[PDB]
Image: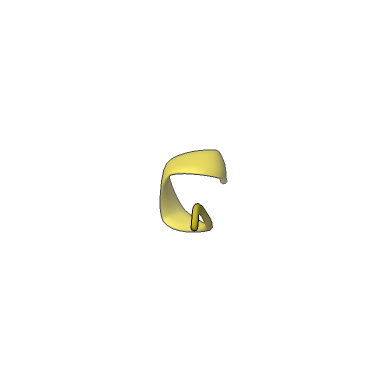
Length: 7
């Protein structure tokens, strides 16, 4: 799960 670390 990656949101922040992908944006």
